[PDB]
Image (cartoon, rainbow, N blue to C red):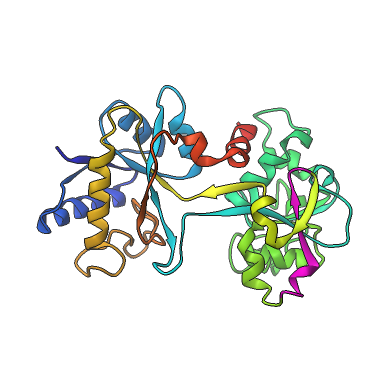
Amino acid sequence: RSVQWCAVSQPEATKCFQWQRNMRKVRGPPVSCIKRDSPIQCIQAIAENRADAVTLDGGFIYEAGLAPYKLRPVAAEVYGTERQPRTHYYAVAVVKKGGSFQLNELQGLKSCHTGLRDTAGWNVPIGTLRPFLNWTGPPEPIEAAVARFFSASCVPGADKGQFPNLCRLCAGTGENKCAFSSQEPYFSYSGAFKCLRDGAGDVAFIRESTVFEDLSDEAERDEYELLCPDNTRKPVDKFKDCHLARVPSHAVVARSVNGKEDAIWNLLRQAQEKFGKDKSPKFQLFGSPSGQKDLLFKDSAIGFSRVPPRIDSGLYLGSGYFTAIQNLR
């Protein structure tokens, strides 16, 4: 037959055509390509058997699995190194030890977010805190509710103009203040942590490893702990037993019924073994051309991982995450 990939963009299309005719050359499994204008359109396409697979993030993993699609992950991107591969992380709420407030009592305190609408620093934390948010649904934006929950925060990317409150704690210079880039000292994960570390804010929403990467001294990081969902605090080494959500990697979604799980997989294994990470200078599966990034697959990816059967979107996501998504719906 052949597996039909779905490109959400036209540059994506070019790398797929590239992929298909490069699979030919190496006499491997064939792949055809489909252009669409959005991840959902691709979800529908695959859904109504116009295509066979597509790589999606958690969010669309959520979406694709819903009726009437019922799509399911079959192959998972893999980050890290061949030496140290990783298919996920944990979204954690860090704080400085010594306090008594818990996750259910963060109202009025100061928060430090990696970025606006980023998963770990936003979608997981703000979706989790949802019960404490005085928010009607749409059309009023969540920022609104968040802006009036915490007394002040740093959310790189937050609209300084509409929601100035979400940029108070930020530390960039002039117009670079609250900007969504390295210009903002409290940007991303390490900036988020430092935000907390500098006493600017009381809680940091980052991932479990930023701590370790940044705090070399074991006795230095005994100065921090984690805020667990069961309204209890814990050391940063107990992240597995004390996190807001377990965030998996982007996964290749496919039909639950008659999905061609194996064709896709047999195609995925081989495409990797030949055009995988620094395997060929002819064509590279994980790598976007100049000006373009994360085409088809995450460039930071280094391989794939088969997803066991009977594992749906919800089970793939995890409750923390899955709940975090619905809560914002």
> Residue 177's quadrant in the figure?
bottom right
Q: Determine whether, in the image, residue 71 is placed left or right of residue 14.
A: right
- Image: 236 above or below 258: below
Image position, residue 71 (x, y; %): 39, 32
- Asked if residue 229 lies in the magenta stretch, the reply is yes
Apparent side of residue 322 relative to residue 288 in the rendered image (left or right): right
User: What residue is at 11 percent from the left and 53 percent from the top?
Assistant: 24
Looking at the image, residue 114 sits to the left or right of residue 275; the answer is right
Tell me what residue is drawn at x 52 percent, y 41 percent: 317
Q: Quadrant of residue 176?
A: bottom right
Q: Splitting the image into 4 quarters, where does residue 318 fall?
A: top right
Stretch in magenta: 218-230
- Residue most toward the top? 68
Nearest the viewer among 93 and 6 is: 93
- The residue lying toward the viewer, choosing from 258 and 45, is 258
On the image, the x and y values in percent for residue 284 come to: 26, 63
Q: Is residue 146 magenta?
A: no
Q: Residue 208: x, y in percent?
A: 64, 59
Residue occupying the point 32% across, 27% down: 257
* Residue closer to the observer: 308 or 65: 308
Screen quadrant of the N terminus: top left
Q: Quadrant of the C terminus?
A: top right
Residue 176 appears in view: no
Q: Position of residue 186 (x, y in %)?
A: 68, 65
